[PDB]
RNA sequence: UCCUUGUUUUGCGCAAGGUGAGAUUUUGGGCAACAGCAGGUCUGUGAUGCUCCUCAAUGUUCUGGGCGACACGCGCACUACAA
RNA sequence: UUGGGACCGAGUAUUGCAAUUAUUGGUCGCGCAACGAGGAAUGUCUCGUAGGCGCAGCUCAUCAAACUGUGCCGAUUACGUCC
């Protein structure tokens, strides 16, 4: 497909649960409310 | 064969180094009051042992470890 | 009543049975359950594996080599048949034949590598009680798989054959030859 | 170079002898001065305890009758010899200076 | 925790058994110090030094087509199907 | 082999902006092509684990022998040492 927070279209696009945050990796680009505890 | 019971009277200790074999002492309960001056032979054993375990002996007059 | 105090496989009785050896009597125990099918936790501690009969232990270690193998319930289906076969062949309770075979196929002395100096050295090393049990079982039921592997026409029957010949001390059995040859090194060298 | 040992690994003091006779080893046949050489006294049994019982049974005039003799020997070893059977071992500084004299 | 009154010289504790759903880092995971590596990443970024591409641009194109996937039957890594 | 599939030809439908076995849950040929537990070497787990089995998510015109997660069937040996 294509991405909306980059225009790269490569370095892999997440479209799981209707979000993109893997053309800007979510570890760097957090505050989506996710956490790791386990 | 000879099948000669003996009770493991105690765990003599640890001998060998493979994690396989232990050296243990056997007491004869096989005797009915027949003369034995041996009288408790040390025997190398293969696999896990526990005190009061009977086991058959195919040999007698064993000193186990020796100098070799 | 009539299944409260009475205990059967489903026709095979545990009154008849006696422990054949006196070396083994705390690693050979009697069955009361009507199938050898397992459902408990069978190991957690160094001896907790000797609280249970040879039957159960054998039926679990009966075969492996999965590909879609049916494991326990399948094994039990073969147990039934093999008991009937052994019964009419010995003309005696099949259970008590198993009791015998496990003891008389077991190696009772061994010899091991334990030397040093760039060289090995062998000494007579007595086999422990639980080991006699375990080793015997494995060898007998290894024989089975090999016998049917591309060969015979027999499915349970090979088990019955082995258990018979083992109890007789006959060297047809896969277990017997091992006891023999090992002791020819372990009582010919100390 | 550096004086590692004051007595130089000897029981020979400076300014006395400067020469003490060589002595063979009971391992490798190596020679070293007597003072350098590592003395031990063995007191080696002629029977193990396990066998002592069995023989004392068959005895009447011996064992019970008289206490069993032992083979006595002095053993003078080389340095290398000693260390390899680990009857002498390396020690920290504070301990190296200690002696126990000729007593065991 | 209790108990075995065992092991524990007093201590720190250890083993077996017991109560019990569950016997010790309760159980399984997740986080994690200090010192670092000339490790990887400038094709993740609006995170960037400089200096290369800056218009017959190679940058760039909902542009067209092709490649990354090829096959002397060649070696290795990983996977799966069987006897 | 009626155990296994991998090659190979013919037909058709489905997906798509575009298919060039993309399609593939399909027909029906070839199977009498390999391979019979497989030298040396070498991997990793002690319990609901190993092993066996299936499903979903993931990627996204379309395809999962992959990856991630849940569930089912479920042992043998050891519970020791430091070589």
Image: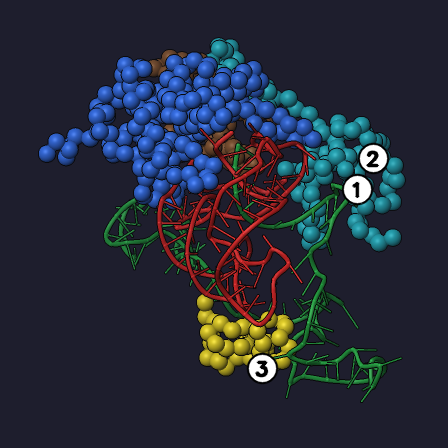
Chain colours: A yellow, B brown, C blue, D cyan, E green, F red
In the rendered image, which quarter contains the C terminus of chain C?
top right
Q: Residue at x 53, y 79 (%)?
A: A30
Give the number of callouts: 3
| Local secondary structure at mark 1 | loop
- The residue labelled by disc 1 is D10
Q: Residue at x 24, y 33 (%)?
A: C34
| 2 and 1 marks on the same chain | yes
Task: Kindly report the distance in space between the C-alpha atoms of the residues bearing marks 2 and 1.
Answer: 9 Å
Q: Chain of mark 2?
A: D
Q: Residue at x 41, y 14 (%)?
A: C169
User: Are the residues at dot 2 and dot 1 in contact (C-beta closer than 8 Å)?
Assistant: yes
Q: Would you say C28 lies left or right of D28 here?
A: left
Examine the image and state in which quarter residue F70 appears.
Answer: bottom left
Location of residue D13 with respect to D54 vertically, above or below: below
Q: Comparing marks 3 and 1, which lies closer to the viewer?
A: 3
Location of residue D100 with respect to F57 vertically, above or below: above
Q: Chain of mark 1?
A: D
Q: Comparing marks 3 and 2, which lies closer to the viewer?
A: 3
Q: Position of residue B59 (x, y in %)?
A: 48, 17
| Local secondary structure at mark 2 | strand
Q: Position of residue C128 (x, y in %)?
A: 44, 28
Q: Residue at x 38, y 35 (%)?
A: C60
- The residue labelled by disc 2 is D33
Q: Residues within 10 Å of mark 1 (few under 14, many from 20)?
A: some
């Amino acid at each position: 497909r294509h991405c909306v927070i980059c225009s790269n279209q490569k370095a892999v696009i997440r479209k799981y649960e209707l979000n993109v945050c893997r053309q800007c990796f979510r570890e760097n680009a957090a505050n989506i409310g996710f956490s790791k505890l386990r | 064969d000879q099948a000669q019971v003996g009770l493991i009277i105690k765990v003599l200790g640890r001998t060998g180094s493979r994690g396989n074999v232990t050296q243990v002492r056997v007491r004869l309960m096989a005797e009915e009051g027949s003369p034995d001056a041996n009288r408790t032979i040390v025997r190398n054993v293969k696999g896990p042992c526990k005190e009061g375990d009977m086991l058959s002996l195919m040999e007698t007059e064993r000193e186990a470890r020796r100098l070799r | 009543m009539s299944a409260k105090a009475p205990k059967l496989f489903n026709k095979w009785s545990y009154e008849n049975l006696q422990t054949t050896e006196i070396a083994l009597s705390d690693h050979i125990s009697k069955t009361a359950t009507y199938v050898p099918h397992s459902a408990g936790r069978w190991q957690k501690k160094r001896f907790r594996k000797a609280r249970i009969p040879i039957v159960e232990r054998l039926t679990n270690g009966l075969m492996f080599k999965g590909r879609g193998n049916g494991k326990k319930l399948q094994a039990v289906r073969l147990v039934k048949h093999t008991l009937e076969i052994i019964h009419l062949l010995t003309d005696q309770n099949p259970l008590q034949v198993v009791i015998d075979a496990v003891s008389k196929g077991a190696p009772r002395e061994d010899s091991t590598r334990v030397g040093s100096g760039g060289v090995v050295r062998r000494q007579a090393v007595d086999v422990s009680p639980m080991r006699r049990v375990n080793e015997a079982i494995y060898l007998m039921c290894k024989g089975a798989r090999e016998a049917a592997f591309r060969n015979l026409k027999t499915l349970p029957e090979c088990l019955a054959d082995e258990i018979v010949n083992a109890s007789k001390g006959s060297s047809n059995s896969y277990a017997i030859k091992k006891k023999d040859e090992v002791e020819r090194v372990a009582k010919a060298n100390r | 170079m550096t004086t590692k040992r004051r007595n130089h690994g000897r029981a020979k003091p400076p300014c006395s002898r400067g020469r003490t006779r060589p002595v063979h080893c009971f391992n490798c046949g190596r020679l070293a001065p007597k003072d350098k050489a590592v003395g031990r006294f063995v007191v080696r049994r002629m029977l193990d305890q396990a066998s002592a019982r069995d023989v004392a049974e068959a005895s009447n005039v011996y064992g019970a009758g008289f206490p069993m003799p032992k083979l006595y020997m002095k053993q003078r070893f080389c340095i290398a010899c000693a260390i390899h059977s680990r009857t002498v071992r390396a020690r920290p500084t504070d301990m190296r200076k200690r002696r126990f004299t000729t007593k065991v």
